[PDB]
Structures are given as structure tokens and as C-alpha cells.
Length: 162
Ligand SMILES: NC(=O)c1ccc[n+]([C@@H]2O[C@H](COP(=O)([O-])OP(=O)(O)OC[C@H]3O[C@@H](n4cnc5c(N)ncnc54)[C@H](OP(=O)(O)O)[C@@H]3O)[C@@H](O)[C@H]2O)c1
Ligand SMILES: COc1cc2c(cc1OC)[C@H](C1CC1)N(C(=O)/C=C/c1cc(Cc3cnc(N)nc3N)cc(OC)c1OC)N=C2
Image (cartoon, rainbow, N blue to C red; front, top):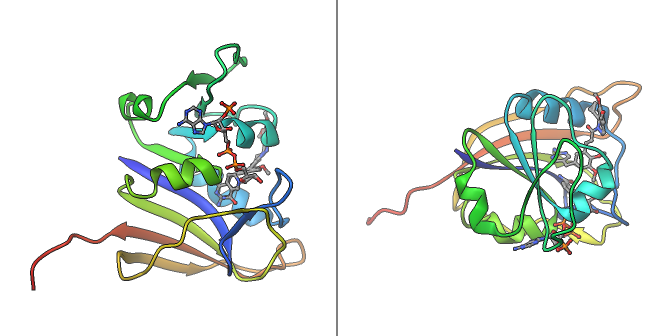
């Protein structure tokens, strides 16, 4: 199974200056719950933003740099290598990988950040015409988690004749 895992705002912003535009602990918890025990594929810039591999899961980084080697990170040099990875693979970011993979994935785990942030990187446009909402769950707000957010699990719709 190949899935997208992403948080994007009302305008599909996902990043600003190589960081998340928002501070939202609940969403990183969401990420931890979904991806622990599985595989993350991410582009080089996303990896450098985080700075180190996320524990208790396989970290795969896509880059054209053959000098790339990081302790605890598997490196690939092409999209095609993604399909050789076993188990549940989450496309983790950033904009470039999402653009490259959105027409290829089975489903998407999207956190809609219900706000408008300054961004310089975006998730590609998509329509609920093409994606079934398997689930939609409002995130709970508190003192530390003040931005409204909704967890979507979207599954690609089958094209059929009507
Ligand atoms: N859910 C979210 O909100 C979320 C998730 C992840 C990231 N982000 C954000 O997204 C932003 C970064 O996105 P980005 O598009 O600038 O960077 P990115 O996709 O993380 O990384 C781009 C790099 O990935 C490598 N790459 C991509 N496609 C490749 C291919 N086909 N073959 C070989 N290498 C390939 C290249 O590395 P080399 O140049 O080293 O070859 C490329 O420069 C950051 O602001 C980050 O905060 C947000
Ligand atoms: C080596 O030790 C640790 C290092 C770390 C951590 C824990 C450790 O040990 C427990 C925490 C962990 C959560 C505790 N951590 C993160 O979660 C980072 C999350 C993160 C994710 C994304 C992708 C992403 C976010 N959202 C959703 N919806 N989809 C996605 N595809 C992007 C980021 O930046 C550009 C991130 O960076 C902010 N950062 C380092």
C-alpha cells in the first residue's frame, strides 16, 4: 500500500522557509500514530528540515546526491525505487514528492489545517470528485492545540462507465 501523508491549510499551503507554518502538536501525534512501524519516503529538503530520522520506522530519503548518507536513513535516487519498498509506504513530503506521487497513490491521510498561513510550498490541487472521504474527524482543541484541524482519510475513486 502506497499512501500520501500531509498537513495542508485552507489554501493548500504545506511549508514556509523549509518548516511547517503552524505549531500543532496534535498533528505530529497523528503522524506518529499513523506511520510508526511503517516506512516514510521524503525528499531531501523535507529531511533536512526535520534534521534527523523519525524513530521506530524506516526513513527513506530521495535525492540525486550520491554522497548522501545519514545514520538511520535509507537513500534512494529515483521515484521507481519507491515501488520496491515493502509494507505500508507513506509519501511524507515535501511539495516536489507530492506533485510526483499524487497520481500514483492509493489513498491520502490529510490533516486540513483550518486556517490561512503564509506559505512558499503547496500540496497539489485535488477534488473530492476524485476521492472518497473514508473518514473525516475534527481534531480536539486545547491550550497547546489552538488551530482547528480535520483529519481526512481519502481513497481514490474507481473510474466506471455510467
Ligand atoms: N505535511 C506537510 O505540511 C509537509 C510535509 C513534508 C514537508 N513539508 C514542507 O515542504 C517543504 C519542502 O518541499 P520541497 O518540494 O521544497 O522539498 P522536498 O520535496 O522535501 O525535497 C526536494 C528534493 O528531493 C529530491 N528529489 C525530489 N524528487 C526527486 C527525484 N525524482 N529524483 C531524485 N531526487 C529527488 C531532490 O533532492 P536533491 O536536490 O538533494 O537531489 C529535491 O531537491 C518544506 O517547507 C517543508 O516544511 C510539509
Ligand atoms: C530523533 O528523535 C526525534 C526527532 C523528532 C521527533 C521525535 C524524536 O524522538 C521521539 C518529533 C516527534 C513527534 C515526537 N519530530 C516530528 O514529529 C517532526 C514532524 C514533521 C513532519 C513533517 C511532515 C508531515 C507533518 N504533518 C503531517 N500531517 N504530515 C506530514 N507528512 C514535516 C516536518 O517539518 C518539515 C516535521 O517537523 C516538524 N521531529 C523530530
